Image: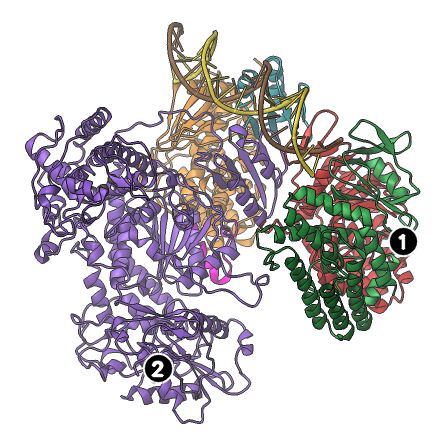
Chain colours: A red, B purple, C green, D orange, E cyan, F brown, G yellow
DNA sequence: ATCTTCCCTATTTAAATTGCT
DNA sequence: AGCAATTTAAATAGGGAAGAT
């Protein structure tokens, strides 16, 4: 049976597109219409997203869920504007460790402890920024980013509600979106439905950080129905709360660099694997959410 | 961690390994996988790639070094992935391999000619005594010697002549004598009782002429005439042509046999004997079924007649020939490239970058690792092994628990069980309690590993679990007694498995000073045998004596001379790598080892002396050592304590000495809060193990975690009265020690148990050495012989430690490192060095280390006994009820701090103390009352 | 094939086997083994299951989740589910944990409702025994079995602590084991490591019970980290606590009958799922958890 | 017959050890003494080398030479201080460009012109340091290295005799070798017959720079038999000037880094390929002899 | 410039294509080569891999962008 | 349906030998 | 000594059928 790899120590992640996923001689493999059967390292896979035109058998889900691979679908509520229901199946056949649910819900029910936990996860945004630096984009130590991080921390320190929190999010994310855009010399309006690369790479990285965040949640047993951020535009649950720790530190710089340096979708996807395994972001989120629940 | 796995496999063994290797890595096409994975993912991929079956052809590359190579895949010598490999690469004057083939084939067709007598036939049928008067190997030797005296034994028709009883069958012909010794010693070696012969015989034939029938073969001798009347039903087709082709092979190659040296002949005939028992036991293990009757060799489990002697001789021949071929033409399976070794050592491990001063392409290496304790010696040994490439080594260590400690270090740093194999051959019942899931410790016996190709030539596919772990291990972290049998055994085929293990693997012997003198002699015999096949010996001992380091170098030099002249290469010398925590030095040494070794020793001494003195020892003046222990405990508590709480170690010599010191200290009236522990070796399985785990967790002073295992709130004297079980293999840190003197290496080791983990220098004195050992009041003639190198041949003129030791002295390894032969009768250190050079000398003697001529005999395994102890019977406690004359007693309950109870287990009592009741007790184990 | 499971009152847990689920003419259908297509009505089903031999496609997944038909992947039989997402209040309009889930959490938190719910789960376990009467098994109305039932009822009602309830639960469970051993003429002692027919048949029947209890806990959104009897460190202890209700009432007589007649494992699986389909055992567990959590 | 690949953009680079070099089925390969046949890409090889126990054949040498691969033999050093004699087969069947040899001759025969070329080539190693800066080891622009190269440039500017050039050559080599020794905290003495890894990595880099220098000289048709720097100690030919232009810039820090990190020789071979390929050191040397020849 | 050639051909068209591309890159193994070569030398390799004959099976990967794919490549 | 095992099915690689230069 | 032609044969891939869930 063995240790079967810790899910923080899995490095492969995939989002398959226009394929039939099946089992051929015990192999998780996706077959395209040209007759090409590409295997998947299912005992090392973090997640397999499924794009439009995809299909998967029962046995492929059976030996992905036995190996702890989270499988989601990018359509349905996957237009990312409402972000209501990205259809995301988890392996709950494995009986998960429970204590992170216990400390998480002790702080959830208590609304003051939920507010404090929300502030910690909002500070994790700037913690992610400082820890994960990029050498092909925005320097974190320049005056604009340091000023807006200081403004974000002094606003989230004196915050009173989740409506006040929703607003601080508006500021951080929107202005980091913008600050990158002005440094990448591009008039940019975030739109999930936009065709430019600066948005299609951003939605691909949104799905990638969705998979990383959901795998980090499921690892600890944490679900999604217990989010820390409640708002009108924050539909989607806890997976987006964990995922937007690493938009502006990881997903957004990689997407902006990709679009500016003319990468293709495949290489942006790979740049995402390289950053998610070189700095070990899954173990980062898993250990940090242990810091979040703790007691 | 980024790896790349390539497959060379045919069959659908390029298919059912593809499922597992495609479960863990992405497919880059053309049967090549490449991707990122964790180290535990590498371990899981190894475990389910090897277990999937035989024929897996997998090479893994981490960056550009090869991670692992499944099978005997040639893979990479310089580049990786060859083209087609067909046949006929080199084809040299192999000579000595043809010599070994001819000797093994000629002897193996003659090894069981002596079962044809009528006594062996009625022994197999079962109407006489199953023990023969003369063993059948000697009868076959008599047959071959009579045939050689009559006809020309190399080129003639065979025909077995009328043979009589011969006391000796060894003549002068060197090659015939080799065949005769292979025939006679295919079950056991001859043993020579003669003192003049043991005194003088050195050469090959000149010792072999003294091997008579009375050395074990001649059991009782009343049916000798029936034991030498013989039938000649072996004259068949295939037996005669096999005998003719092997005899002519020997005939054609024996011209290079006379150009060999004594050392060569001994090592080559040892290899021939090992291959001959390998083939004999391999054919005797399996059941062949068919038989041509009228003559028989072996019996089955039902006792029926099987394995007729013609096809038995033919089967033993081909199996021994195949044994020889696979043991002489093996590219053995090595360990994984551990990625947590190859980076830089930081801080106190920064000396481990000395491997970047050693050549990575040397065929031989003799490491003398003189680094101090706590610096990571075994990790540095693994680093030195991995500097030359992939690792294949046998970490032979004293004690079970030290092998457990090195295994736990290997596990938590980088080594999985696909490369490591921890072998302790007793199946101890010491289990870990509290939490099985939250343990993260207790290295166990599974060895997913990889079965080597040498298992097919061993009897009945090696064995079960233990010998598979022995032979097939890339890294074999073992107790040392699974390796010292390579040099040879009395009775049976127990030599072959450690012999074939040490043939293709390096040898790493750590802290060889804790072994006995005969134990060190047979360990240097093992070093010589390991160097005989080009493997590298790593010795790791800080307190090395020049004598020891020298005789181990000379054993390695004789072995490398064997290996150099065996492959017809000119001997350039031995790559000696002196190593400590202050530096390294690699020199090609063929001569003048002594001046270079003493210069490195002096450099290490000067690198130890300008550091602050950590162990200041005062020899007490108080004659009576009981009250000397009292006064020294009071003084070193009043001087050395951590806020009123002090830890003391009373190192004494023997068990009744320990209980005497304990029973005095328990009845000792003082204002000090003495809390007494007994820490000797005579204890029941449960009780002993419990003491160990407690002591290891309370004397750990690298952190302040111990404050919670003892009552440090109240000023208390925590005193541990112990025998030499504390000075070997214990990671203990006492505030101070009171030492009963037995030997100077005991003084240095118990200095190493004081301030082992801290770095604070003592102010006045942290060691109080007793004036006399307690055997002075029992035997004033000799008192230091128990746990010391004093003896009947080496007597101190005075037993006063003011006369034989410095009154104030900084105790370190310097006195043991220097080496003094003069004034050995009135100083302990020069007494130690004297014995070490007078027993481990550069002679062959009979119990010595250069042993030549006697390897042919059973003498180095009888008169030099590994772990030579007393009779030792074992009184066993079964569920609270003792077996023999034990009688449980009650301890003094005055100052006992901790007392663990025991119900199962066993105590090891010498036969001398079996006469009286050992009187087992819960606090202190065995005594005389 | 096509299989209907009533779960709460009106929604039906559809189980689909040996079929390919896709979108035909704008609505979700599936081609079966016999080459005949079957559609699915969106109104009458909420849970739809994919058994062995089953593949689903991406737009079928999206349109099923947009119609409130939330999909799960299961081993063939319908009660061995390994992959799903979490029930919300609505699948598209919002993301909130279900009322049942929140009620369970609150009940678990305050110590008195946790003790009362532990007593109640054992009350309904005794109810289950009587409710699901078998034919081959022992009589529940027999004097010895009724004495064991009243002993358990007295012991649960008079207890004020959980370890007393654990001792009483073990006494009741192994007393029913002893009663069924007295029926089937054997020395039966419950150990997981034994290779006899009764112990290993009870073990794999218990695994089936864990699967159906996992489906029942998932179908109301109850998470797998809030056990009543078992400890907080027991991984998936709520699955074991809910499966305890039907372990000694359904799994134990079926397993002892299966070891008595000595048939193979797959036909024991079909007997277990036949008993689950015939008497609506999952619906019994769903109503059991509603009555536990609603209080 | 096409452009036959120009020499400055040839990339592959080997020194073959303990293998007989042959041709199988079209391609040049080397066969070791275990049956392993590794192919040599002769169309892109710059040089091959032959260590102890090596043996090349006739048509293999022909396919290297007609393609234009310079081949040498590593052994031959028999003195105590000097890399004595390396035997080197020039591909002269390819008829070379001529006027670069005429320019080299017109500077070689004029003594004041040879001294002037000696001057610029001595500061060429100084600018090599400035251009080729490694990421490890020393920094070139520190005070000690700049002070010693400034003293070297000041002394070689006022130099008027070749023996003064040899003396200043000796102080330069002692200064660099010892400063690298200081950085890597070792005691260093340059002996070609030493077992220390800093020494035989330096001899391996001596062979590598020798091969690079004959390929650079043969690419412009320049013979080794016109040494513009000569002396009693310095008697190797023009290879011992165009080879040790790039010791203290390329090889010696790379040799010290390889002897500090301490894996096998193959990582040093591949690191020499990587740095001679990434910075185009061969084309850099060829272009430097180009701006030498026409000035 | 670091490229990688993958060959998926059949003997003896595999024999001859391995013969031809093994003159340009290091044999990383199992009919797959990887090595450093200039892009106009890559065009030279392309030109005499076309002229070498039919049924030939070569794909390229500069970084991972397919620099040239020869034949009806499966990929 | 999906997937597995096995039997054709022959298509597809590797070795082997041997004149020829 | 490399190679070529050319045989010889071992193995790889695929498709169809049938049996499992
Ligand atoms: Mn015998
Ligand atoms: Mn025999």
Left or right: residue D76 compared with residue C203: left
Res. A160 in view: yes
Pointer 1 chain: C
Pointer 2 chain: B
**Mark linked to residue D187:** none
Question: Circle 1 sits in a helix, a strand or a loop, which is it?
Answer: loop
* Of the pair B727 and D224, the residue shown nearer to us: B727
Left or right: residue C171 compared with residue B828: right
Res. E62 in view: no
- Residue B333 lies in what quarter of the image? top left
**C-alpha distance separating marks 1 and 2:** 76 Å
Question: Circle 2 sits in a helix, a strand or a loop, which is it?
Answer: helix
Give residue B768's position: percent from left, percent from top. Answer: 35, 82
For the residues labelled 1 and 2, say whether their Cβ atoms are less than 8 Å apart: no
Query: Is B755 one of the magenta-colored residues?
Result: no
* Of the pair B649 and C209, the residue shown nearer to us: C209
Q: Which residues are magenta?
A: B339-357
- Residue C187 lies in what quarter of the image? bottom right
Give residue C41's position: percent from left, percent from top. Answer: 91, 38
Give residue D142's position: percent from left, percent from top. Answer: 56, 52
Residue bearing the label numbered 1: C89
- Residue A165 lies in what quarter of the image? bottom right
* Of the pair B312 and A53, the residue shown nearer to us: B312
On whether disc 1 and disc 2 are found on a single subunit, the reply is: no
**Mark linked to residue B659:** 2
């Amino acid at each position: 049976m063995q240790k079967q790899i810790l899910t923080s120590q899995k490095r492969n992640m995939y989002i398959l597109s226009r394929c039939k996923v099946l089992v051929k001689n015990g192999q998780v493999c996706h077959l395209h219409e040209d007759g090409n059967v590409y295997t998947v390292p299912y005992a090392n896979t973090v997640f397999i997203g499924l794009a439009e035109g995809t299909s998967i058998t029962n046995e492929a889900m059976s030996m992905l869920a036995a190996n702890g691979v989270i499988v989601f679908w990018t359509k349905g509520g996957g237009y990312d504007m409402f972000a209501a229901d990205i259809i995301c199946h988890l392996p709950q056949a494995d009986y998960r460790p429970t204590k992170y649910m216990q400390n998480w819900v002790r702080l959830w029910l208590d609304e003051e402890k939920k507010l404090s936990a929300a502030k910690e996860i909002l500070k994790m945004r700037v913690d992610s920024l400082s820890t994960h630096v990029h050498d092909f984009g925005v320097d974190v130590e320049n005056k604009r980013v340091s000023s807006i991080v200081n403004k974000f921390d002094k606003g989230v320190t004196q915050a009173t509600s989740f409506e006040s929190l929703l607003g601080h999010e508006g500021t951080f994310v929107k202005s980091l979106y913008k600050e990158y855009a002005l440094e990448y010399e591009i008039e940019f309006k975030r739109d999930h439905k936009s065709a430019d690369n600066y948005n299609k790479f951003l939605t691909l990285g949104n799905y990638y950080a969705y998979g990383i965040a959901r795998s980090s949640l499921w690892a600890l047993g944490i679900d999604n129905s217990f989010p820390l951020l409640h708002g009108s535009t924050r539909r989607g649950g806890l997976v987006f709360d964990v995922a937007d720790i690493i938009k502006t530190s990881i997903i957004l710089p990689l997407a902006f660099h990709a679009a500016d340096q003319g990468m293709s979708n495949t290489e942006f996807k790979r740049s995402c694997v390289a950053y998610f395994d070189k700095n070990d972001i899954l173990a980062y989120l898993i250990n940090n959410i242990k810091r979040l629940c703790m007691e | 961690m980024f790896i790349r796995i390539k497959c060379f496999s045919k069959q659908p063994i390029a298919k059912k390994v593809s499922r597992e290797v495609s479960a863990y890595l992405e497919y880059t096409g053309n049967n090549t996988w490449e991707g990122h994975i964790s180290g535990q993912g590498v371990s899981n991929l190894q475990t389910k790639l090897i277990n999937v079956g035989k024929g897996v052809k997998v090479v893994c590359n981490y960056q550009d070094k090869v991670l692992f190579a499944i099978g005997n895949v040639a893979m990479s010598d310089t580049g990786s992935v060859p083209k087609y490999t067909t046949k006929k690469v080199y084809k040299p004057d192999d000579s000595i391999f043809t010599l070994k083939q001819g000797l093994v084939g000629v002897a193996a067709l003659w090894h069981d000619l002596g079962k044809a007598n009528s006594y062996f036939q009625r022994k197999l049928r079962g109407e006489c005594n199953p023990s023969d008067p003369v063993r059948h190997e000697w009868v076959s030797g008599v047959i071959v010697s009579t045939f050689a005296k009559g006809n020309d034994w190399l080129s003639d028709d065979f025909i077995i002549p009328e043979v009589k009883h011969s006391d000796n069958v060894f003549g002068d012909d060197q090659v015939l004598n080799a065949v005769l010794w292979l025939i006679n010693t295919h079950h056991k070696k001859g043993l020579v009782e003669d003192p003049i012969y043991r005194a003088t015989k050195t050469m090959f034939t000149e010792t072999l002429q003294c091997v008579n029938v009375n050395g074990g073969w001649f059991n009782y001798g009343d049916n000798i005439d029936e034991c030498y009347k013989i039938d000649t039903s072996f004259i068949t087709d295939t037996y005669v042509k096999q005998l003719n082709r092997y005899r002519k092979k020997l005939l054609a190659t024996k011209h290079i046999w006379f150009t060999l040296g004594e050392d060569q002949k001994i090592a080559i005939l040892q290899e021939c004997r090992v291959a001959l028992m390998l083939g004999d036991s391999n054919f005797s293990s399996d059941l062949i079924g068919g038989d041509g009757s009228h003559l028989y060799a072996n019996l089955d489990e039902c006792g029926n007649l099987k394995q007729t002697l013609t096809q038995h001789l033919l089967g033993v021949t081909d199996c021994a020939l195949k044994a020889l071929f696979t043991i002489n033409h093996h590219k053995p399976v090595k360990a994984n490239f551990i990625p947590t070794i190859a980076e830089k050592g930081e801080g106190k491990f920064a000396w481990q970058n000395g491997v970047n001063m050693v050549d990575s392409s040397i065929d031989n290496m003799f490491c003398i690792n003189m680094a101090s304790t706590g610096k990571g010696k075994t990790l540095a040994n693994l680093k030195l092994l991995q500097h030359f490439g992939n690792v294949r080594c046998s970490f032979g260590l004293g004690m079970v628990s030290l092998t457990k400690q090195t295994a736990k270090q290997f596990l938590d740093m980088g080594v999985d069980y696909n490369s490591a194999a921890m072998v302790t051959g007793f199946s101890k019942s010491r289990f870990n309690l509290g939490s099985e899931s939250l343990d993260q410790d207790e290295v166990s016996v599974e060895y997913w590993g990889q079965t080597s190709s040498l298992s097919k030539v061993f009897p009945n596919n090696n064995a079960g679990f233990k010998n598979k772990k022995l032979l097939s291990a890339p890294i074999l972290v073992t107790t040392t007694d699974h390796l010292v049998k390579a040099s040879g055994v009395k009775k049976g085929n127990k030599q072959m498995l450690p012999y074939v293990r040490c043939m293709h693997s390096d040898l790493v012997l750590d802290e060889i000073d804790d072994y006995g003198i005969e134990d060190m002699v047979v360990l240097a015999r093992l070093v010589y045998l390991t160097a005989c096949y080009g493997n590298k010996v790593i010795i790791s001992s800080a307190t090395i004596t020049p004598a020891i380091s020298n005789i181990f170098y000379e054993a390695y030099s004789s072995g490398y001379k064997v290996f150099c002249a065996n492959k017809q290469t000119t001997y350039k010398g031995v790559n000696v790598v002196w190593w400590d925590e202050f530096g390294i030095k690699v020199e090609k040494v063929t001569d003048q080892f002594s001046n270079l070794n003493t210069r490195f020793v002096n450099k290490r001494i000067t690198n130890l002396l300008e550091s602050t003195p950590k162990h200041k020892a005062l020899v007490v003046d108080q004659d009576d050592n009981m009250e000397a222990v009292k006064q020294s405990i009071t003084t070193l508590h009043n001087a050395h304590n951590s806020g009123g709480v002090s830890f003391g170690l009373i190192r004494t010599t023997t068990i009744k000495d320990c209980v005497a010191v304990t029973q005095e200290l328990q009845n000792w009236e003082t204002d000090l809060s003495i809390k007494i522990l007994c820490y000797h070796s005579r204890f029941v399985g449960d009780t002993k193990a419990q003491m160990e785990e407690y002591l290891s967790k309370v004397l750990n002073r690298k952190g302040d975690e111990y404050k919670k295992f003892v009552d440090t709130t109240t000023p208390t004297a925590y005193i541990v009265v112990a025998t030499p079980v504390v000075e070997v293999g214990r990671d203990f840190d006492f505030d101070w020690a009171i030492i009963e003197p037995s030997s100077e290496r005991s003084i240095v080791q118990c200095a190493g148990r004081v301030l082992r983990h801290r770095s604070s220098t003592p102010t006045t004195h942290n060691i109080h050495i007793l004036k006399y050992p307690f055997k002075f009041y029992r035997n004033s003639n000799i008192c230091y012989d128990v746990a010391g190198y004093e003896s009947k041949g080496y007597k101190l003129k005075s037993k006063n430690m003011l006369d034989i030791y410095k009154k104030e002295s900084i105790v370190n390894s310097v006195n043991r490192l220097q080496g003094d032969a003069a004034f050995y009768t009135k100083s302990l250190t020069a007494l130690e060095h004297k014995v070490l050079l007078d027993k481990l000398t550069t002679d062959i003697a009979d119990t010595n280390v250069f042993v030549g001529g006697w390897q042919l005999t059973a003498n180095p395994h009888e008169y030099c006994k590994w772990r030579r102890g007393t009779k030792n019977e074992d009184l066993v406690l079964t569920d609270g009820k003792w077996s023999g004359n034990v009688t449980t007693t009650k301890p003094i309950q005055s100052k006992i701090w901790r007392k663990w109870q025991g119900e199962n287990g066993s105590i090891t009592v010498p036969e001398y103390l079996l006469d009286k009741t050992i009187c087992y007790n819960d606090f202190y184990g065995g005594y005389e009352n």
